[PDB]
Amino acid sequence: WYLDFVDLNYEPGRDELIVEYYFEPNGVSPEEAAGRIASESSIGTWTTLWKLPEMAKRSMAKVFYLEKHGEGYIAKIAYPLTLFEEGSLVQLFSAVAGNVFGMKALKNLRLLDFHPPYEYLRHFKGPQFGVQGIREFMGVKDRPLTATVPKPKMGWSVEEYAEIAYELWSGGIDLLKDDENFTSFPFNRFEERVRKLYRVRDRVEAETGETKEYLINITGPVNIMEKRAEMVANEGGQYVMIDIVVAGWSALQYMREVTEDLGLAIHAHRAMHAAFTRNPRHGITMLALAKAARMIGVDQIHTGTAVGKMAGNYEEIKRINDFLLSKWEHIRPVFPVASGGLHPGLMPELIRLFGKDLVIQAGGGVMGHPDGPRAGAKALRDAIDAAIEGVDLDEKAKSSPELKKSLR
Amino acid sequence: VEWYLDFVDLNYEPGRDELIVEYYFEPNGVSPEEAAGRIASESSIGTLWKLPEMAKRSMAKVFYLEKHGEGYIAKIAYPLTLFEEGSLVQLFSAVAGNVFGMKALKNLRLLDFHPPYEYLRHFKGPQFGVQGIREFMGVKDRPLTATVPKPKMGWSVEEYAEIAYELWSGGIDLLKDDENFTSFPFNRFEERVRKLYRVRDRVEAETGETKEYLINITGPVNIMEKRAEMVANEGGQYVMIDIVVAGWSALQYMREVTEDLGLAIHAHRAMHAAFTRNPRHGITMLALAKAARMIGVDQIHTGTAVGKMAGNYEEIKRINDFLLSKWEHIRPVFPVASGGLHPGLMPELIRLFGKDLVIQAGGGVMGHPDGPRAGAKALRDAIDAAIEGVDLDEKAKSSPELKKSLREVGLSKA
Amino acid sequence: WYLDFVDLNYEPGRDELIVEYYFEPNGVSPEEAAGRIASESSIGTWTTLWKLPEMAKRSMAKVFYLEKHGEGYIAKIAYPLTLFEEGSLVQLFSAVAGNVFGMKALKNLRLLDFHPPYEYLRHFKGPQFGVQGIREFMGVKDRPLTATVPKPKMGWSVEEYAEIAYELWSGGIDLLKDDENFTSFPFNRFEERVRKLYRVRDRVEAETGETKEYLINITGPVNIMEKRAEMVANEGGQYVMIDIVVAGWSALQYMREVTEDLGLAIHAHRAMHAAFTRNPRHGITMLALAKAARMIGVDQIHTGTAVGKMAGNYEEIKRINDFLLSKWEHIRPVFPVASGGLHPGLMPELIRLFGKDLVIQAGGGVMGHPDGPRAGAKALRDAIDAAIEGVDLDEKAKSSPELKKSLR
């Protein structure tokens, strides 16, 4: 039966969903392995007896491309839309990213990418704001945005958090960002944080004439996340942060509706992703993850950077960033968020390689500045201004004491 | 102009994900090809500033154009980018809107449409259909029977209850309100619902047979919803809506309501003939029945082959065939036959149109010489006879009520 | 029995509803045909046995006028109010415009007009705003209002729609108008359109000191239409557009209550009407449609124009326009909306023939202006100013470059 699912001359219609897998077979032929992925991700097996169901035949997936690739194989598989509950990314992932990973006839299986047809994709809204909508409400037309996570990442009282925030925002940071694990604690309850931090936010706005925002972490059981998002909207926030991998796709799809009602942008933290995106032979790629997140509609998502302290291989990151920012029917582009050991001196290189449409998360460089967080923020903003203006950092530094000290 | 000809390409092969509409038309002062492109244009993107990418992609295409009688038939392909999926209202605004008013046509008739799978899948179709209705009614094989009281207006709730008792007791399956009969100071809907389902339950207890009520909930939508809620609360399994007068927007919403409440929909088609009757202009009954079946009415009036209604056999059969055909996940709909039907016509009716019908024969039944109960019995008897292949004159020997109906009809003709 | 319904000497009371029909009999006498319309639209048939119902006799319709008219006949029929559920235009149309159209004893049947008595009409509110209420909230006291539908009529993104809108409004258009088929699409969702277009609206108001509005198309299944109307009211809109024939009378009556609660005027698009108003022998007239729409209470409705590109016979259109604008107890007058190939050069004639109480929809002329939509709007506003002021277009054109170019 597994071979009924393999037709290397099949030409998929524009209304079929395509998934690309890498795999290594275990004691079976490449074709049998491929067929097995297709059957398991579609109708399973049958032509014996007791009534074949009427839509089974029309719902068969088909392997239409199979080629050797290094130590394994790449297959592309076409899925008729009769297999799917439209609007449920959850059910899509149960089909194409479910039981297939555990099959003993494969040593390894990686979902590399997928391509939803227009009739699947039209039932997703994508980002509510995207790059352009964020740039509008932030009032930042050309340069990348800046973000900072306080260090240490845990243990502040609300008052202590408010003071750091005041300093970061005042020095030039656009977005305060909670750490992925920083949700709500006895010494820093979410409700008290929301009531205080947005007062400090509004004060800095009045004093500087620059828009400031807060990537506040609403991550929790979904009912709690919804209540936290309502609190944020009620205080005048326009962003919520969600750890999307830990929270999961069912909650994210629902929160996308909540954020639509409340006018909130979503910053997606991708903590836990490496558990299945890191292994080059087995799991789901960051690309496929980013695609699903963009389709549902996160407005910004972490992708990594190119340095040594973050390391980060250039081709993979570039590829994801390019996808996030590409035209894709009605789905608004998503800001890549660059983080990892970033600091003012790396800004020209970051921006040469990755463009101006970025959220630059540079908490280390900012917090660890010898004159304090406010000075570190200033320094970062100055390195970005110089990168965009084509000005050498050492030249800028002669008119920016804060940047000067950072480059030492 | 040459712009309108950009919408015409008679070698185009439409993909399986495009919606097709078939029109008859007669041009008025332009060529046939220019008329057809005008139709395609006006029902898609219409006609300095940057022509958006989506507009180019969303152009309809005339891919078939042949002469037909005194005019022409065109088939036009519509990408689904033109449509708000789930909204039959919006589809009809595009393909059945301003297009009828076009000065470049003398006449335009929407003949039929074919939604692709990706459009159709966002409609549920009938909640019950033929098989759902036969299950809740407990009637496995024969046609169902319905009767609208005569006269059609003016009854108190008590008088209506008494007629209903007789009709159901005599064997009618479905009491039917007239299309004009909603709620009046002398017969308020709330009172009628609270009384008639007690009568219904009484008749079920006495006969062992299931009885139902095609009760007319037609009104402003908020009123129809409230009336549907009252029917469900009294144990009713059907509501009747005059779907042409009420309209598509209300009907789509009411199909959600009846999903929640577990109610079947009987669609009365009053006013349809204002646009379905003219063979050169309007919307065919076929196209209308298709839209109603997609949304999901469970029974709909189509017409009969009778003395009184000498309706076209071939058009009626085409509609009934469509209603009963397999159509993906969309359940089949019962055709409702009516128009001057009496017991003597049951064998011809069933021979020509089959057993999957609701037969509304109010006139024969109400006009029986021994009263409505006897008319109901006579109708049921003629139907059993037709199904078992027994001559009506043979059946009449064991059924005095049928005997009398057959005799009196014979005494009523020249 | 059909003859019991004919009394050519009957004088209807002021409390009876009168309907006027055109018909052609098919094998029966004019009187029998007329009687058949009356019976079918009232009590049907009966005097045999099994209890005549108590209110049947008092609910009989009566043909009281029958005269030859060309190739057929006109009948007027009086209906006692016992036949009707008061406040339900739906039930009125089921009686008088229902099964009568399909009767085989008539070759043709047209409902020409109806006349509700005060005790029927008092249960309808008519337009919430009408001509005077619109003129008040638009701040436009004498001249006709202007409207424009973007071309092409479909396929814009929200951002592209907002830019056209900015230009139209800025040049002088009063009302942006969505096309009848332009509701909500993946590339232009209603909720995102509402949130953006009213921001651009408020900006143009601030910059020009002129009120601007949006005939935004809420047409859909009724629950969806209600949610869309709430969205519009919430953003500060005062108008919604409904395709009333496609949506239908049940939804319209309900929406009239929704718009009452929300303070919204209704613009009625009449798409699909020609399916039954166009045939001179059979259907319902535009007059009767306009009457029902006015009674429920649309504030503006399309009637057509007098040119060549719209063609439009003058007597019929004038007659409807006159009715819409006439005193009619408590029912406010309704703006006729003139559309069809209109452009600045036709304004003096349009206004001579049809008056200043019009909404002039002139999308072709405006969008197709050689200097752009903004210039086209300006040109239209200038042709209207000149028409009202008694000024020759070629004279105006010497102080209006935009109009000058349009007249070429």
Image (cartoon, coloured by chain):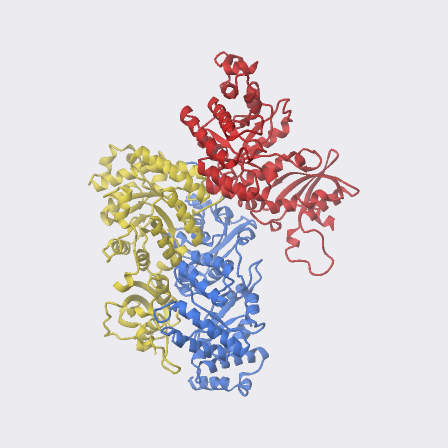
Chain colours: A red, B blue, C yellow
Residue located farthest toward the left when viewing the structure as drawn: C390
Residue B106 location, x and y as percent?
38, 56
Quadrant showing the C terminus of chain B: bottom left
Is residue B281 visible to us here? Answer: no
Nearer-the-camera pick, B50 or B268: B268
Tag count in the figure? 0
Quadrant showing the N terminus of chain B: top left
Residue located farthest toward the front when viewing the structure as drawn: A186
- Based on the displayed image, in which of its 4 quarters is residue B272 positioned? bottom left
Left/right of residue A348 with respect to residue B309 in the rendered view: right
Nearer-the-camera pick, A381 or B251: A381
- Based on the displayed image, in which of its 4 quarters is residue C376 positioned? top left
Is residue B362 visible to us here? Answer: yes
Q: Is residue A355 above or below residue C9?
A: above
Residue A204 location, x and y as percent?
44, 26
Nearer-the-camera pick, A220 or B255: A220
Residue C386 location, x and y as percent?
23, 39
Residue A363 location, x and y as percent?
56, 25
Residue located farthest toward the bottom when viewing the structure as drawn: B397
**Identity of the residue drawn at 34% across and 78% down:** C1
Q: Is residue A100 above or below residue B245?
A: above
